[PDB]
Image (cartoon, rainbow over all chains, first blue to last red; front, side, top):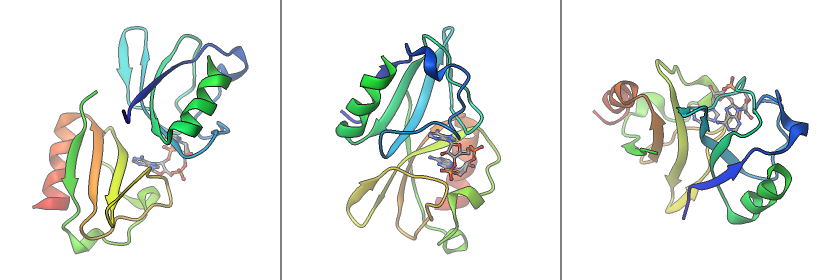
Length: 70
Length: 71
Ligand SMILES: Nc1ncnc2c1ncn2[C@@H]1O[C@@H]2COP(=O)(O)O[C@H]3[C@@H](O)[C@H](n4cnc5c(N)ncnc54)O[C@@H]3COP(=O)(O)O[C@H]2[C@H]1O
């Protein structure tokens, strides 16, 4: 698998924009599924509680990010 | 999530930075496969001749990118 899904269930990251997010490693947000819509994420895209994040990167950082976010 | 592969066959864009690419649409480069390895693309990342660009986004702009990069 190369596309992983992570739930954004951490209140500490609400309204935090991708351009300021402190990534656990080399990761790109491929899509964010929010309110039944699939968004192509960019720098000023803000995380929201309940977001379904579709991410790609090495399993390590993905796992790392997963722990912090959900 | 649809991903599309685009070959970087246009020397016009070689060495150009992702932060400096003129995007005319809603698109993200999910992966670049370069020198037999699969890499995660960022702002500094350069397009290099022969790159296999894996992209996601508005299909209309994917199509324009394919014109620019591999036609
Ligand atoms: N995979 C990709 N596909 C297409 N273009 C790409 C790209 N990765 C980087 N870029 C382009 O480079 C900018 C520079 O990227 P950078 O990684 O330095 O700087 C970024 C980055 O760390 C964060 N960001 C934006 N989108 C992101 C994403 N999908 N995943 C992770 N971080 C993102 O916001 C900073 C400013 O974002 P902004 O989009 O307004 O500005 C973008 C975008 O035009």
